[PDB]
Image (cartoon, coloured by chain):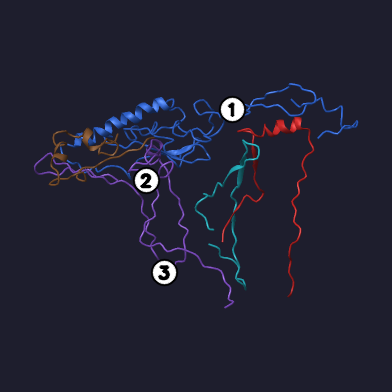
């Protein structure tokens, strides 16, 4: 039945932490570490079949 | 004539064999490649569980898979009558 | 063997094998993402796509 | 007893520990004895190779004690690089309190120069434990030969040699 | 550990120099380099 969705004004948003650069630039360089990095998993730790 | 459609682009290979080298760069420079039979790639044991995901199979076809192993024979004749046997896989 | 209840309509037996998905985000430069994804009861090659 | 193959360790990567050793066949040469003038060569070229893989086994790694240990400390297996690089800040820690809340809005620092930096270590918080991480497998268990197969039935045999094996119990 | 001309060097070096001369003294009558294996190698 005659209906459609189109698009008109698209935007991205980013709410950063308003931090003091003294602690911001130190720990982004400490996350810049070879050992201290980031890892993210899932609750669905599962594969799929068809 | 105002008739509109998209192209159906592909390719048609037949009389060729798909070759892969074994070097770091992957190039068939001579028989021995850079990571073919190096030092790690000669002493340690490994497995192969590689897939062959393919196109429409209207009839049952045997997917003929080769592996580039080594079979070099040295024909020894130090005697007037006997061929000495050395065969490697 | 999946000897199950006979049903009226064609249904997809969408089985899930619990296989861990880990992506380690190595960030040794400010704004560079270099990652590898791997699973444990799953080799990253042999699969249905 | 007389002609065995050099044993080759089978691997499982994410565990870190090798499963067990096995003999080589898909490159093993023809043993249909060529004659009395080449039998000493096929048994002789192999004989010096048996000492090639024997000598390096004591050099590359310390001689076998626990043949396959999962609970593994780091000594020859290398813990990753411990070196940090520390840089300063464009803005100071204590030279910012004077301005913004009072009136003057803020948007080496070319206002009031100061030099203050603090360096902290990059190393893995506590030492490496468990199996081999990246690539230290060849340097840990080099292909080594037991030239007299199962010589000694009830006491001990090639134990952790089996891939269907854990360190806790045999079988 | 490799004997059958697989990690050994070019034909002229290891082999007996008695008829290495005759490999290119006998010109078109016996132009032979496929008769013996020529092993070529790459750095590690």
Number of numbered labels in the structure image: 3
Give the x, y percent position of residue C42.
53, 50
Which residue is painted at 76% across and 58% down in the image?
A: A9
Q: Which chain is purple?
A: B
Q: Which chain is blue?
A: D
Q: Nearer the viewer, mark 1 or mark 3?
A: 3
- On the image, which quarter does residue A22 sit in? top right
Q: Secondary structure at mark 1?
A: loop
- Chain designation of label 1: D
Image quarter (top left, top right, bottom left or bottom right) of the C terminus of chain C = bottom right
Mark 1 nearby-residue class (10 Å; few <14, some 14–19, many ≥20): few
Real-space CA distance between mark 1 and mark 2, rounded to the nearest whole angstrom: 43 Å
Name chain A's colour.
red
Which residue is most to the bottom?
B1
What residue is shown with label 3? Answer: B59
Nearer-the-camera pick, A47 or C5? A47
Mark 3 nearby-residue class (10 Å; few <14, some 14–19, many ≥20): few
Residue D31: mark: none
- Chain designation of label 3: B
Query: Of callouts 3 and 2, which one flags the residue occurring earlier in the amino acid sequence?
Result: 2
- On the image, which quarter does residue D153 sit in? top left
Which residue is painted at 55% across and 33% down in the image?
A: D130
Name chain E's colour.
brown
Residue B28: mark: 2
Q: Secondary structure at mark 2?
A: loop
Name chain C's colour.
cyan
What residue is shown with label 1? Answer: D127
Nearer-the-camera pick, D38 or D23? D38
Real-space CA distance between mark 3 and mark 2, rounded to the nearest whole angstrom: 35 Å
């Amino acid at each position: 039945d005659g209906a459609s969705i189109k698009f008109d004004s698209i935007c991205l948003y980013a709410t950063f932490f308003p931090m003091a650069h003294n602690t911001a630039s130190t720990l982004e360089a400490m996350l810049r570490n070879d050992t201290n990095d980031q890892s993210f998993n899932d609750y669905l730790s599962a594969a799929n079949m068809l | 004539t105002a008739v509109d459609s998209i192209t159906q682009k592909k390719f048609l290979c037949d009389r060729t064999l798909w070759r892969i080298p074994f070097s770091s760069n992957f190039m068939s420079m001579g028989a021995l490649t850079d990571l073919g039979q190096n030092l790690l790639y000669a002493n340690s044991a490994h497995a192969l569980d590689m897939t062959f995901e393919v196109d429409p199979m209207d009839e049952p076809t045997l997917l003929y898979v080769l592996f580039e192993v080594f079979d070099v024979v040295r024909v020894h004749r130090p005697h007037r009558g006997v061929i000495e046997t050395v065969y490697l896989r | 063997t999946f000897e199950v209840d006979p049903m009226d309509e064609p249904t997809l037996l969408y089985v899930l094998f619990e296989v861990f998905d880990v992506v380690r985000v190595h960030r040794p430069h400010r704004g560079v993402i270099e990652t590898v994804y791997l699973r444990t009861p799953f080799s990253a090659g042999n699969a249905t796509t | 007893k007389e002609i065995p193959t050099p044993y080759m360790w089978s691997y499982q990567p994410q565990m870190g520990l090798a499963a067990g050793a096995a003999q080589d066949y898909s490159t093993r040469i023809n043993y249909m004895s060529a004659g009395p003038h080449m039998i000493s060569r096929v048994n002789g070229i192999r004989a010096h190779r048996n000492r090639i893989l024997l000598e390096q086994a004591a050099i590359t790694t310390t001689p076998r004690n626990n043949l396959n240990p999962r609970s593994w400390p780091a000594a020859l297996v290398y813990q990753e690089s411990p070196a940090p690089t520390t840089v300063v800040l464009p803005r100071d820690a204590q030279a910012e309190v004077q301005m913004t809340n009072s009136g003057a809005q803020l948007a080496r620092p070319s206002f009031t120069p100061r030099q203050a930096i603090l360096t902290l270590q990059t190393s893995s918080s506590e030492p490496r434990s468990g199996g081999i991480g990246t690539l230290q497998f060849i340097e840990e268990f080099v292909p080594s030969v037991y030239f007299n197969p199962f010589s000694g039935p009830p006491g001990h045999y090639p134990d952790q040699f089996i891939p269907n094996f854990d360190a806790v119990k045999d079988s | 550990w490799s004997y059958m001309h697989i990690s050994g060097q070019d034909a002229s070096e290891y082999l007996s120099p008695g008829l290495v001369q005759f490999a290119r003294a006998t010109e078109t009558y016996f132009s032979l380099n496929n008769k013996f294996r020529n092993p070529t190698v790459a750095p590690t």
